[PDB]
Amino acid sequence: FLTAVSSIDTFLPVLNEAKLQWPTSALAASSEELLGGYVGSQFYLQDGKYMQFQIAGSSNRCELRQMIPDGGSEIGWAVDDGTTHTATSSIVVPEQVDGVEEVTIMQIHSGEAPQLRISWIRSKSLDGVAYEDFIMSTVRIGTGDSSDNFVKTHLADRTAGAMSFQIDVKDSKLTITVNGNVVVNGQDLSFWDGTDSCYFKAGAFNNNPTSESATARIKFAALAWVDH
């Protein structure tokens, strides 16, 4: 059998506060199943140290969804409760195979929409400028579909080596730090004031692939979700 992510200590804190959704939004493994050695080609310990997610198919996913710790049910939090909600990761995004076009690797999501997606993108124009093989943030500042509902930012070109991300939400402001540098500084989340159903996600959520069989693959060297 492939080696399970829970066979080492590194990911136990996040697995204790997550369920796995795979290959759709439906539950694949409870927190206790994750801590108890759930494993497959979609979710296994790679190179002895990475929690690796793999998924093919349009809008399919292999993704952790934040839960109340210690076997609890789904968590929901607010963007302006006075605390800081923080997700920290170290991610190796390998070169993606032909057919994979965009992979969402971290989110803030709520009952009805994603407040934030961090995604790898093969190629895209942002604000009249072309970028290739890069990491992007997409923030929703409304629920509609026109462009005024989104703020998109080039976070970094994809690197061979691990790339760290810190997502901080405090007092209706979002900050994203990449490799220790603030890239998104205090993006307004006040559109979501009153929402108490937000939560973190991380893994691989395959968006708009050109082929249904192309398998997205994302490796986490570290992942934690905390409330300060």
Image: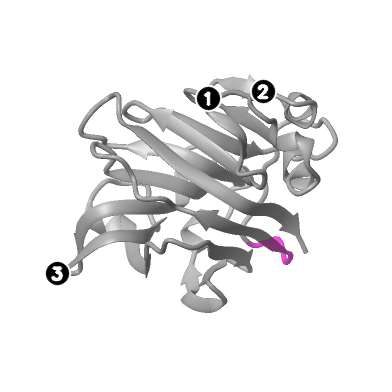
Task: Look at label 2 and name its amino acid.
Answer: Ala
Viewed as shown, does residue 38 lie left or right of 134?
A: right
* Neighbourhood count class around disc 2 (C-alpha, 10 Å): few under 14, some 14–19, many 20 upward: some
Q: Determine if residue 108 is in view.
A: no
Q: Which residue shows up at 26% across the image and 36% down it?
A: 208
Q: Which residue shows up at 36% across the image and 30% down it?
A: 59
Q: Check the picture and name the quadrant holding the C terminus.
A: bottom right
Label 1, label 2: how many angstroms apart (C-alpha)?
A: 8 Å
Q: Which residue is mark 3?
A: 128
- The disc placed on residue 92 is none
Q: Position of residue 103 (x, y in %)?
A: 38, 44
Q: Is residue 61 magenta?
A: no
Q: Which range is magenta? A: 80-85
- The disc placed on residue 22 is 1
Q: Which residue shows up at 47% across the image and 70% down it?
A: 187
Task: Look at label 3 and name its amino acid.
Answer: Gly
Pointer 1 with pointer 2, Cβ within 8 A: yes
Viewed as shown, does residue 214 lie left or right of 87?
A: left
Task: Look at label 1 and name its amino acid.
Answer: Trp
Q: Check the picture and name the quadrant holding the N terminus.
A: top right
Pointer 1 or 2: first along the chain: 1
Q: 160 or 175, which lies in front?
A: 160
